[PDB]
Image (cartoon, helix red, strand yellow):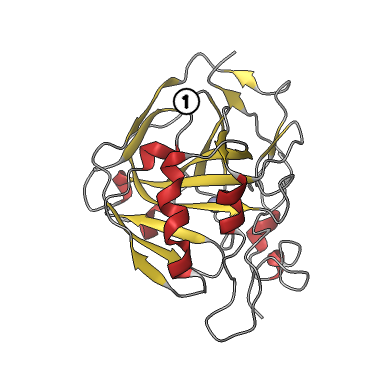
Amino acid sequence: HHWGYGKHNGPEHWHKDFPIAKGERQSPVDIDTHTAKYDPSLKPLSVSYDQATSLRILNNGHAFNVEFDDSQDKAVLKGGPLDGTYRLIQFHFHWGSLDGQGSEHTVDKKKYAAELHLVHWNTKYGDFGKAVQQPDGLAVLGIFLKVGSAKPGLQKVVDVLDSIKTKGKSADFTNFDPRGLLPESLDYWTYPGSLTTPPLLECVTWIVLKEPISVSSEQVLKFRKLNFNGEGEPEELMVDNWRPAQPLKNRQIKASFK
Ligand SMILES: [Zn+2]
């Protein structure tokens, strides 16, 4: 059948239907902090989310997405490694069944409990679908989650998860401010990579923040109560929806800080 995260349809099988799974710039990767290099040429990173307009939250059977209105430059990412303007279209998470796993990227082989992906597309290509046919189509801002104190800006997302328990469910989710999900520091690593799920397209400039956010044990537990299945099908808890680290191959990770 179709792809997911189980023994019979998980990451080790994806290459049969998406041969680019074995390509030259796949994601995620392990970030070896001693081999990353500070790059003084990177420009200041600009996360400009004051006019972000959230619309809806959806369980898609792989994770849940909070979607935004991207018909104008209301929430954009620029600077850093980026040329041009990238519009926020959605964010989602990947997380584990246990606190010691769940992130896609790792840092010196350390796994975090979860990872937040804020997905943006390069406005020069007109729409998201054209962007994913380009090698500089997308920029994804990745943020690690560790378990500790609650993240107040996450709580509204946690509060609505009961209404999207199963695949295909959605709920109105307006007036959500994604600035509440950021850590204090915007220091980051960056490298060229891919989508971390099928179709695994190699279109992404990854920007991974050094500083994790903390979320509470009750907040991560609520992610783990979601279902991969649809309503009325047998229950399969949505956990461990992460792809493991892939070969770096011919890429150097750059750092915005020393
Ligand atoms: Zn993701």
- The residue drawn where x is 21% and y is 48% is 72
**Nearest to the observer: residue 10 or residue 27:** 10
In the rendered image, residue 40, in percent from the top left (x then y), is placed at 51, 13
Query: Left or right: where does residue 170 sit relative to residue 116?
Result: left
Asked if 89 appears above or below 80 in the picture, the reply is below
Give the amino acid at mark 1: Leu
**Nearest to the observer: residue 134 or residue 167:** 167
Query: Left or right: where does residue 35 sit relative to residue 168?
Result: right
In the rendered image, residue 148, in percent from the top left (x then y), is placed at 62, 36
Quadrant of the frame with the C terminus: top right
In the rendered image, residue 21, in percent from the top left (x then y), is placed at 67, 57
Asked if 115 appears above or below 149 in the picture, the reply is below
Badge 1: residue crowd in 10 Å (few <14, some 14–19, many ≥20): some
Asked if one can make out residue 135 in the rendered structure from this viewpoint, the answer is: yes
Asked if one can make out residue 137 in the rendered structure from this viewpoint, the answer is: no
- The residue drawn where x is 40% and y is 38% is 180
- The residue drawn where x is 65% and y is 68% is 237
